[PDB]
Image 1 (cartoon, rainbow over the protein chains, first blue to last red):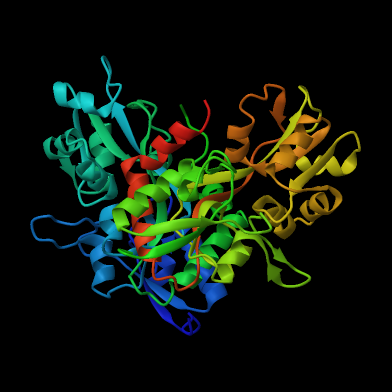
Image 2 (cartoon, rainbow over the protein chains, first blue to last red):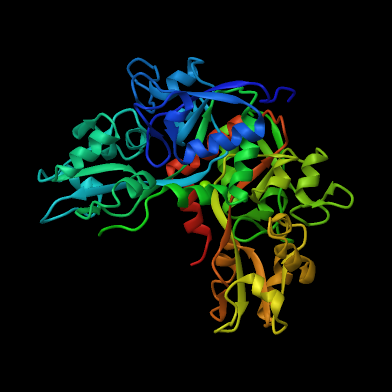
Length: 255
Length: 247
Ligand SMILES: [Mg+2]
């Protein structure tokens, strides 16, 4: 109520995930190392709400999931829970596991799970077909939203997909493995759309499934949620989110 | 929420809510996608509930002359209700007064007209002609978005168009011909499914959500948000849209 963001210094959790965030590893310092759709949103928020900020990456370079053996979180989620950060500023997918531990901002983008495949010859219509064949290998990135949704899906065949697939380290590794061929990568629509635009030998496996949002992550009881929510809604209503997606997402296709 | 009683603001808006005006008692007068959501929430969280309609039968908007709200929004601000359970569109004006739950459906503004082969390509072209009339429903979200749009030609559309009482009046006027009705995609999709001579004018514009409305500092927001997100994740929202929307 009384608290606002004027004069505050926010620590923002993030990682590279194009086109939401690009992180330069040399030739820059501090916030200047960061660019992308989410960075543009943060810059505007900082101008309008009067805060300064820095970005903090999790050492494990994970987005975050709950380990059912240890009951501990990792990734950006863990950094937020541990008060290393105040908000997670990225394409953070909405899922129930995360919601049990953190809050979400007003959302900025609808997204679904999308599976893609590289390979000549017989192909697949739906991801569960992977379980009854051995032509294609497949995988999801560990400690990231798609893995969590497949593991919590009430049809435990989706947990089989996760358990019997390759555990991929991060998006670069997943895309490298996909490009190696005879592989199905199961991830998120907007991420794949942007990053695989030139991969003319990569095709869809069925339709997108599951419905969720990208939002920012906020700790429970954050004094800043109301303001962030209001301002993100205004961004959406004013067309800013759409303008930034057009700015940053890849256009055309050589294909 | 276990043991609690929630007063829920709502009105008829098919296929989200159907209200029977006779032949029923209490909660059983209501049905539809939103009712099915409320029933499941009630079972899972353990609250009882009733529905309360605003006397003015409006969704609600802020009158910039009086700086007062009407409709379901006003009933919530007046503490006549605890939550608004309907397809409540997200807009900044409402956000200045109330909170929203986690959303359950994307929606856009859509314009429609009767008669094949309309010559209109975009709604602002209406300002430069007088073959067609047009309008929006008063004290409802599309009116608010057009009035608050950066491009004040959208305010012109509202000010120079017909103020429609409600969805029935609007569809009636649409079906009467030579009239462009500007409203919300999902509502129009459902309610005009059988109108095979009604057509879109331009593309949908504006991006918003349907959510429930909550008073600021509600003690119930966290739980409602969590359970609505779980409904989306489990596929329940999509199953209900398939159940209720035509067809
Ligand atoms: Mg949405």
